[PDB]
Length: 257
Ligand SMILES: NCCCN(CCc1ccccc1)CC(=O)N(CCc1ccc(S(N)(=O)=O)cc1)Cc1ccc(F)cc1
Ligand SMILES: [Zn+2]
Image (cartoon, rainbow, N blue to C red; front, side, top):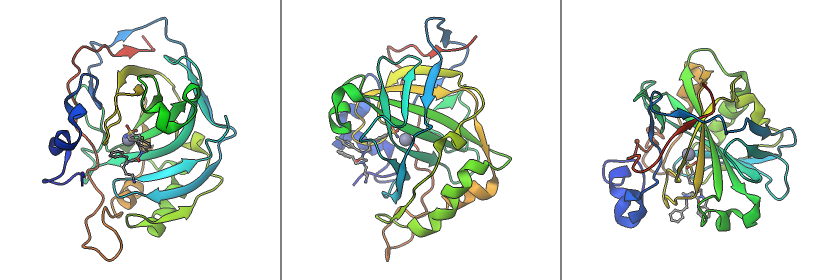
């Protein structure tokens, strides 16, 4: 099965998922000098007031905080998007050390982690149908740097002890994802893919320029999770990021001057 180790990591994924070598793969390096300001882009609309979190799950490659997406409760619209995209889950990618962990890079800089808020286009009815479409998903990516603690992340950090191993889940109601957003919604956007198998080319990526700060203690708790299941040899869940992929025939657009 695919993963992040030497024998099953990103350089191997193409054997089971040939789209790994496709024309719109993610993540990518964001070259800030080449990204063009697009005055036609609209401000992003992040409407999370009615978000309903339900559960947190260790799925063996990250942890997902899952939301009720049976109604338009937490939605992303505007920006580069046409239509309405419903929040289904968020998760992170992070490193073994603070100098790596993000999937996107900025002028080749790697951040300590990257948060992905995953949304699907309601015109396709369900997430499984949406991933089959080139405009099916919108993922909002937010970089994490290590410095001051992020108060709105602590409730996530403190439940991780309860989902240490693959397949464990825990009730996770009443979590407000607005507490994970930076001040500015300035962003870069480009067409890309899921960054884990099946690597489907169905994502409009929206990557915020402003990182959030988390504390060393917060990210250290991410790094105590396990890729393995209970009662299996311990493999710390670290370095669960895919490196930057070729940009090919794509333009990254900036919402800001
Ligand atoms: N236990 C989790 C096991 C890993 N993986 C199994 C999927 C899979 C299917 C076929 C073959 C291989 C693997 C996760 C999963 O199931 N997802 C999440 C999809 C996803 C969302 C966001 C990003 S990201 N990092 O933000 O770009 C990446 C990926 C739901 C889904 C639902 C319906 C689909 F048709 C496809 C995926
Ligand atoms: Zn992700």
